[PDB]
Every structure is written in structure tokens, then in C-alpha cells.
Amino acid sequence: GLASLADFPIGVAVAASGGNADIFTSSARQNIVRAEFNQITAENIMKMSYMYSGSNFSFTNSDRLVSWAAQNGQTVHGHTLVWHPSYQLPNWASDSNANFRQDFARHIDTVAAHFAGQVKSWDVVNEALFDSADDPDGRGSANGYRQSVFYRQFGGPEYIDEAFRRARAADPTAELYYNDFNTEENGAKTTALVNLVQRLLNNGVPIDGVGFQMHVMNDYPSIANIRQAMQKIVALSPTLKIKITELDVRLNNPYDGNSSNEYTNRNDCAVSCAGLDRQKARYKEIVQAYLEVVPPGRRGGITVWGIADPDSWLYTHQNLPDWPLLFNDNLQPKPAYQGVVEALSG
Ligand SMILES: [Ca+2]
Image (tube, rainbow, N blue to C red):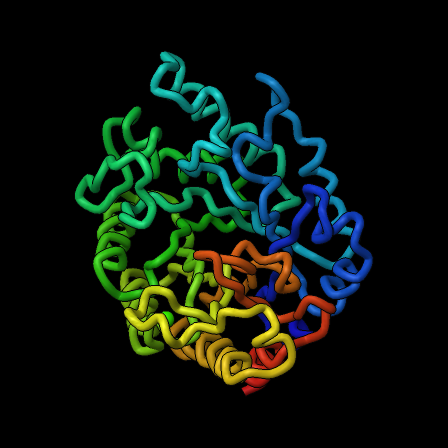
């Protein structure tokens, strides 16, 4: 399968919360993972609050998944040690908590140490950059940084430095990544990413690489912009790695100012459409851009954000259907899959 075609990780996000996509119950999905991939990311169950049961740490469910990976040919990318969304914040992660900075330290120290030797790499900090699409409380930018509870408590971006040093100290063997979305657009957020990373480098922070989530549409952003955005980060350092962490590709673009070019019906791309053919070319050009701009040393992996289309967080978006992944609803490989094969093989 796909992983045989590369000498860097080829990974997939897996579900473990019941429902049809849950990897523990779906032998069809288990079989695809073992045949095609050599790394998994937990789609959900390694987020912050999942490390607790009440006020105590609990690693039961995540240990099960990490063990499954070790038994079935997969390394693990840990997603994620620090991340703002309140749905996954531990209860300690609150402006009402006098013990914040200590509880933050305990979090990173405990979790990173717990998984030492079992988890290859981590998203140490995820989504530290401001994004208007992504500001439900209307906090606004602090010179490009998200004013998350971590930022507010530390009084600035120093939490990022601390998270990285603590992770490094707790598990010196893991590759440590900073992860974010929309940074492939090569606009304002990419600039903010440059600022963020440069500051970490200036401070001597043990960041090993940068993750681009790569939640793209078929025709936006342009591949030239994707390529240049990566180039800008590669140029910051002679050793900084680049990983594509959450790749998926939406046929439909509701943000292009043209509402006449959508596939509005689930049946539209059930079998064949211009969209699935473009999606093949889109996966292929992105895996090509990555290879062309990221030197081999420095390639930390490519991961797609789920196995089969109905598992995707983008299966429906903006009340429209989409088909974002490499396998279809019947778990058959799509043209997308072939696009990856062609890219990997040259
Ligand atoms: Ca459109």
C-alpha cells in the first residue's frame, strides 16, 4: 500500500468513540490501516481533556489505541498536548484557576512522560495563531497570536516556549511539532506563522518541526501559494522538519464568490464527476509540492484526516455534501488514492 511507497510516515487519523468509524469495532477500517498506512493519529481521543477522568489522569482509552498501533504496524503521532478549544480543555485550564501555570506544567510533564517510547512525535502546541474564521468569542488578534486561555494566563506567547521545553524534558526521544491550519494560504496567517516560529528559534526553544494541517479545497488555495508557504518555513532553519498532519480535500468551495459551481447532491460524486478527477490531481500536486520543497531529511510525514468519506469531519459542511478522503463510503479507493500513489512513486 501507500506506506510502502515512501520512506517517511504515511498516516491516517482514526476514530475511537463509537459509531461506524471506530477503529476498534470496524474490521474493514482496521484492514485498510494495516494495508496502507504506517502511522496513526487519534482523531479525538488524545486531546487534552481525554487525559483525565474527573480530576485524575486517566490513560486507559488512549493506551488501548497506542497499544493497538504497536501491534498493527503503526507508529503514533500524538494530537495534542496544548490546544485552546473549550470542548477539550481540562477543567484546570481556566482563568478562574490560581494554580494554572502549575497544572499546565503537570499536564505536559505527565502526558509526555507517560507516552515516552510509544509515541513518535507530538503536536506540542496546536493552533496558536489568530484566525477570524475561528474566533467565536470575538477576542481578536494579539499581533497574530490567538488570545487563548494559555496566552491570557501566561500574559503572552511564552506558554509555547514552555510547552516545548517541558515536552522535550519529559520525552527527549519524541519529535516535537507546532501545528496549525490556513498557514498554507500564504497570506496573513502564514506571516504570523513566520513570526511565531522565528521567535521560538530566537529563544532557543526545542521545536523540531512545523505541521501544516492542509485542510484544502480542490482549487483553493493555489498550489503556488501552498508551495511558497512551505518554502517560507523551510527557509527559517536548516533542520526544521515539515509534516502534513491533517490532509483532506473538499470538492466544493463556498468561499469563492460563485455559488453556481457546487455539487449540491450526495449522488453527484457517488460514482464519477469532474470533481473526483480534480481531487486526484489535487492530492497528487500537493504530495508533489511537499516532496519538491521539503528536503528528504526533513520530511516528517503525510497524514490524511480519516479513512473513508463518511468518517470525515467535512463529509458535510456548510450544509453541503463533500467527499474529502481517499476511500469512499463503501471503503473503495478513489481517484484520490491513485493521485497519492502517482506522486509517491514519481
Ligand atoms: Ca463555489
